[PDB]
Image: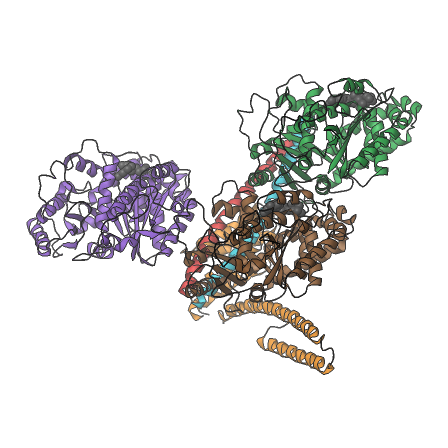
Chain colours: A brown, B purple, C green, D red, E cyan, F orange
Amino acid sequence: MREIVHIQGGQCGNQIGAKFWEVVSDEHGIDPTGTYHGDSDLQLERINVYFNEATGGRYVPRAILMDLEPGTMDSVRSGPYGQIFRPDNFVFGQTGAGNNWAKGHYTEGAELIDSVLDVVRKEAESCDCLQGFQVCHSLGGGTGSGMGTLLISKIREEYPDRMMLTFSVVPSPKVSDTVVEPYNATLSVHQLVENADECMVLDNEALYDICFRTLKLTTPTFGDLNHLISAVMSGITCCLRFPGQLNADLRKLAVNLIPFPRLHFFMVGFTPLTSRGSQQYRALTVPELTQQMWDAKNMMCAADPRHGRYLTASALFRGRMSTKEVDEQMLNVQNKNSSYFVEWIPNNVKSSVCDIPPKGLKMSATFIGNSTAIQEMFKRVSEQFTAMFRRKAFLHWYTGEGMDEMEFTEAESNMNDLVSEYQQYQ
Amino acid sequence: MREIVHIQGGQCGNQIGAKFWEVVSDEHGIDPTGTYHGDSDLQLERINVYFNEATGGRYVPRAILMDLEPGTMDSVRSGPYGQIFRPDNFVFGQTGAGNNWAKGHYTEGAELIDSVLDVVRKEAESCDCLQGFQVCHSLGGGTGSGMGTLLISKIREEYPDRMMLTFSVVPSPKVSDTVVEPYNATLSVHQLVENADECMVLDNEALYDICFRTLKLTTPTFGDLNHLISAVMSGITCCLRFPGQLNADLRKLAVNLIPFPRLHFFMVGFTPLTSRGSQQYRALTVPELTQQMWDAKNMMCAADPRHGRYLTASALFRGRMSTKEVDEQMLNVQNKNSSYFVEWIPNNVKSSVCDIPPKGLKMSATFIGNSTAIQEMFKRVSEQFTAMFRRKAFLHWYTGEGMDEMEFTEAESNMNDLVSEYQQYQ
Amino acid sequence: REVISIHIGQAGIQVGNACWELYCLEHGIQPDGQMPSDKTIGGGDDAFNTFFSETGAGKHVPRCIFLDLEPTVVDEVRTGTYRQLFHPEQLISGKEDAANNFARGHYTIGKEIVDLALDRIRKLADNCTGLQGFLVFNAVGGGTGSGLGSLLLERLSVDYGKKSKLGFTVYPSPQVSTAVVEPYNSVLSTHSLLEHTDVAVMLDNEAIYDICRRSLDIERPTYTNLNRLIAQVISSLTASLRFDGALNVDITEFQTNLVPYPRIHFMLSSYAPIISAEKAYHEQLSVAEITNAAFEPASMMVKCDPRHGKYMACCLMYRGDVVPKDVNASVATIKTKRTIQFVDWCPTGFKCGINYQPPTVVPGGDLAKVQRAVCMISNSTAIGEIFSRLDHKFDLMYAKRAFVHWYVGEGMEEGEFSEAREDLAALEKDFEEVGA
Amino acid sequence: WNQEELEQWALAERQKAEDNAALEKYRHADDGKVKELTLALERVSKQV
Amino acid sequence: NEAMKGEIAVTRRAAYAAEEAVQKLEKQKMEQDFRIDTLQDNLKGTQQQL
Amino acid sequence: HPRTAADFEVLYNELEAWRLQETRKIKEAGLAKEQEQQVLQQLLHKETKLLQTIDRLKINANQENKEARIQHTLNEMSKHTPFTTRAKELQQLYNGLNLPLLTVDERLDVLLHVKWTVKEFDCDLTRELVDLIDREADLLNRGRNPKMLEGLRKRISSLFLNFIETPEFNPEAVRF
Ligand SMILES: Nc1nc2c(ncn2[C@@H]2O[C@H](COP(=O)(O)OP(=O)(O)OP(=O)(O)O)[C@@H](O)[C@H]2O)c(=O)[nH]1
Ligand SMILES: Nc1nc2c(ncn2[C@@H]2O[C@H](COP(=O)(O)OP(=O)(O)O)[C@@H](O)[C@H]2O)c(=O)[nH]1
Ligand SMILES: Nc1nc2c(ncn2[C@@H]2O[C@H](COP(=O)(O)OP(=O)(O)O)[C@@H](O)[C@H]2O)c(=O)[nH]1
Ligand SMILES: [Mg+2]
């Protein structure tokens, strides 16, 4: 009865959201044909949050897919569980922009967003009572970062009192994939810090190291690199779909995790994470799950979480357990690591539980931490941006598209001030 | 409840621990697949002294395999009962010390201890009530003598109020398998005298003699020697796992057998070791057990007790015995061999009785003596150290690896004063 | 997402003749026009849209024109194995050669054929829908490649302008050469290509001779080998458009990522693994060593030493079985390599694209068949060195006014000679200021 | 002259390489110190 | 002389690469030194609190 | 620029008075029955900016008070018993470390003096102190910008201060 509208932009957004939709559809128990097969009754009770009955069981997902290159929609439609998305939700141009934030945010943001907004408005007014918008995309691209950011601004202007969860993957220092990464990242941050309700930032080398150590995969491809993110995205939305001892919705998470409206860049985790070889030698219980949660090499951001303090943190548990031991473990972690927790807040950690584990398991958790150590993920981009902008390198591709140097100056100023206030709260 | 965590070091340590876990698994009834397949109820009562419950009756040992070459790790994995260990515990540097004490204590130790200490700390914190640490190693190799003692020093500095019982197989003069045996052994005892707590001395020459005469074995492979050492280990760790008419835990044995804090090198045996052509002939009684116990040709060391006086002795019997019989037998031995016992210590023998004898047998016993006869084993290594130090042989391989020229002199000095402090109280 | 190809001069014609052979082999098109109806290799009816166009009953025709004044090679193609494939009127043959005379190919004879060439290029563009740009092939040391090429580049920029132009230009070599007017023609084509070619990638027959001598162990190579391997390079570059992969790109991105300045587009090409058929099943194929081979100094298609300058932006287009983790590790290693250096004008200067398509070798060829291959395109600052070694000989010739009577009698004076010389000097100044 | 210049640049590169090696060893020692400091702080906080 | 000049250029670029690598490593070293300073300050404060 | 908790109290109270006057004016306006809440939100955001500025000033004042009070304790370590004379000598060494080490030669000289002085006791702390001294000495001898040796110099100063704040090393530290 609470409604989440899931938008996905860019190649990253498309693939990640496709994985997320396969996982969620499987967990609610619907086959790729489009019908329902969930044996239990706890599954039909909340299909309305992500699915709409069309006629005779054809539960079409509520999602918007947007980019500028036909290949991504072709691949999504071809892939498994890709025969369920409604074709009319493939709001889409024809050209493709490529690595150009200005091109994707100024030119095509005119002749494509004019229809993306129409599709989003129709889909939102279709449901009764909205809960919020859940949008997944990248920062180092052109068709996902700029286009998605302009969509974010438009939808914040349209619907003011709605949650916004931006699953954004940010560029990496070591993982070099293009040269306009600092430019696109700074430009996207300059509007995310202004409009986005909260950004669950992600990266790539943290996930690669996760797949190396915590899973011992030898060739971690995108098909699982995005499976992890899909699991996290499914696990964050547990209360809106399943009962539990202590429900907590997105508004609750924002209230508990945002001391100030410019402090909403979360780093995210997920437990348990273990290799298939040792999935038989470990004990599944809260004492081990909590220790796995509160680890540096377990987070999904290239920011060593001990490099500062935690302004706030949240834990979302799934599965039958003891809300005595959950609270005791949270308090134990606080007292043991009191140095790495800010002082002027008591009980920096919120913990909410639910009675339904994910399919194929028996117990799970999810970690969402708003810590000041996330400042480095922005400091590296800021220093790269300064180094590149001291030379006006690759600048003409923006200046001949319509952007000026004032946009870059403003982006740098906002980036620096938010990083400075992160440093202050430490 | 009270806990023992088993660290195995080096090739010899790995093999001995593998055989020891093979033995204890069947003593408790655990299937090598990992499940429980026992018969009696009383087996289960204390399997938390050695095991953990992973997922649905998957009992797994609390052991850490530590070494620098992966060949012995591969052999252990290939061998029987290999699929019982947690693969996370498997830690190795893959390079190899090459029987270089300096390399294994300064070069590769500094790089692999950072992980082996993490693993042992994880086991300790997974525990609740730690009795102490159990260690298996050698005194003639690079990893066993250097990295083993480095890990022992690390454990003593971290947990200063937990015992370590360590089975050290020492280089006997006439069964030497390498040329740097004293250079390794003296340097290792340098730290074993001031860090460890019970340095249970073993040597393969005595085991060879036992297999020749008492067992009348013709071709004893290392399997049988490892079996004998495992039997000694089980005999030591039995009051912790089964009820008895008297109790003697590790701490009690230590406090009874250590009069002065530098005399903690115990020498042991085991009864009844019967040749399988005489097992059908002899009828086993408590006098027979004590006869084979105090039989000098059964002690698992090349330190004949006829040449030295006994400071303390302990006998851990297993089987429903008569306590009057056991105590009067100890008295009879003490009154017969009236010259081998210290005069200022009345009733040098402490005897404990447990109710559950080992598998198959109906009566057993283990002897742990702290005598002054052991100082021959140190004289025979100090003489060799002086021999190969008089003309500076093989020094550069340690000098250029990180060690100075004064540590060897310090080790020789500690050998000399240790032998002097046994001579003083002989 | 179609891109049309135009082939100017003898070198361009032969390179295109090799390229379209490779392309028809890839997409399974028979040498008589139509795809077989009994054997179905590969998949994707939109895979051939980029380079071919379907007509009626399965008769495909390529989107490439072959324009030349001398009719010899053109009618050799017209009578050769590729008769049915090409459209009969996409092959333009004049009457008299430009004859190493840039003036004769740019002013007098050129103006009477470019009108026809454009009247057909625009027809091809109208037939096309998603025009992704133009690709040009020309030998700057000749008469048709320089004169006709310069005229046609000027008119295409005047007409469309807003679309990309990838130019694979065959500059002369340091010593190897087969003319005497190479410096003159090369500078007079440089002045025009520098400010019109959207992305100018260079080739060199000397460098390709070195590559095919050390690697293929063909100690006596003709032009067919060079044309074949250049065709391999072009196919590796267009594989992103033509197929699907884990991380695909296109032309627009290729310019947007590798051209840091409006006037700095002179980027070294390379390919790997250049391996014969007798060692491909011996040597171990993985991304680390193939990347090292691609970055090996004596594996550049242009005979210049790349350690001299600093890279600006490298594009590694991988084809076949590649999982991005190992390419990331190889990227880290190559950036940590001691001999190659970047410039603080660009902190992160790599770009990796990947496609799920192994390379295809033409039957009866010389390259072996493999799993994976990396085509590398890097912007550097040794192109300043190549332009300088060309400029020395050009001004040495211009000292005595040798061979200039042909130009003055054909239609150009010395004013534009001085102009082009000064322009190339300014280009060298640009490179030397930017690099350090 | 050119041979002299080559000698000079080889010496300069050797000096820079030695500097890099020393700095790397320092960095590794500092990482070890990071680990030990973290452990000590944890233990002292628990005692508090 | 041509080959010698080529070698001169290659060695010069190698030396400059070494210099820039040392500069980057020094910056990272200084950051880690700040980190050690903070983790020692916290330890001293906790000891005084005990 | 505050330094005392009393002055911080004055700043806090005047800011709270300003808040009360602003909200009183907003209330006495008696208008905009829908923009009233937006004006209130903007006023709170202004308050947050000013409070963050006060927090920054508090951080600066805390650091400067810490340095000043360490100097004051060093002075009280002086106000002619032999222990107090050794304390004055160690104060001289600490001031040598404190002053801007603008000259590499004087930097090396004072490091040499403090290394000689420290190497006398050598129980546990001198190991890391000597390691850091040698680190700075090597990175100055090979030639690196002293502006890049900032955190390492800070660490040397901190370890030397910890060495001074020790009974055996400074045989009067039982005072504090
Ligand atoms: N690498 C390579 N070079 C070629 C090939 N074909 C021609 N060339 C080169 O092209 C250079 C100059 O072109 P030309 O041979 O003069 O032919 P053109 O460019 O059409 O100029 P004109 O024929 O005089 O009008 C020559 O030096 C050849 O080396 C080829 O297939 N491969
Ligand atoms: N984890 C993950 N990262 C991706 C995926 N696809 C692209 N990326 C990364 O996203 C960054 C930029 O995304 P990009 O391809 O430009 O998105 P686009 O704008 O849609 O083209 C690159 O650094 C890639 O490494 C994916 O499927 N999974
Ligand atoms: N009891 C027993 N002793 C062994 C076995 N294998 C080797 N040894 C002894 O261990 C000594 C060599 O130790 P070494 O393997 O070099 O120690 P490392 O260098 O730490 O691996 C030899 O003197 C052997 O007598 C075994 O399987 N059982
Ligand atoms: Mg010609």
Q: Position of residue C323 (x, y in %)?
A: 56, 39
**Image position, residue B355 (x, y; %):** 17, 54
Where on the picture, by quarter, is residue E5?
top right
Q: Nearer the viewer, residue A415 or C62?
A: C62
Query: Depth check: B108 or C39 in front?
Result: C39
**Above or below A336: residue B257:** above
Q: Residue A94: x percent and y percent?
A: 73, 45
Dividing the image into four equal quarters, which quarter contains ligand 1? top right
Q: Is residue C192 above or below residue B417?
A: above
Q: Is residue A158 visible?
A: yes
Give the quarter of the figure containing the N terminus of chain A.
Answer: bottom right
Residue C169 lies left or right of residue C289; in this view the side is right
Count of numbered tags: 0
Q: Residue at x 66, y 25 (%)?
A: C36
Residue E1 can be seen, yes or no: no
Q: Please, is residue C203 above or below residue B95 in the view?
A: above
- Tell me the residue at 70%/46% (across/down): A68
Where in the figure is residue B282, as x and y percent of width and height? 9, 41
Residue at the outermost front position: A56
Is C430 left, or right, of B164 in this rendering?
A: right
Locate residue C39 relative to residue B138 in the image: left or right: right
- Residue B37 vs residue B378, the one in the foreground: B37
Q: Is residue C131 left or right of residue F166?
A: right
Question: Split into 4 quadrants, where in the image is the C terminus of chain A?
Answer: bottom right
